Length: 80
Ligand SMILES: [Zn+2]
Ligand SMILES: [Zn+2]
Image (cartoon, rainbow, N blue to C red; front, side, top):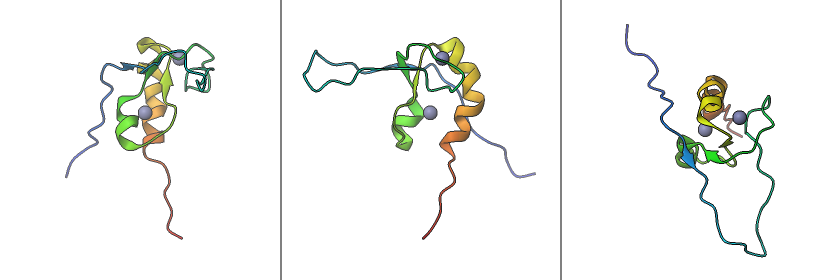
């Protein structure tokens, strides 16, 4: 054999909030489709990859959703 995947689900991170600016952005739900909870955490690997949103509600929930979330990281790119 050669090698296997090197994916990992480390401790999530808090969503960098801001002051009560006029041009603020409300509404924050768990990224998971089957989770309508308040999103407070964010995906670390996402910030690096370059994906929008990616906000979780809790680690306990992230650990699970990660099973599918990780798949999102490897989207289906095309060449036109
Ligand atoms: Zn992510
Ligand atoms: Zn959640």
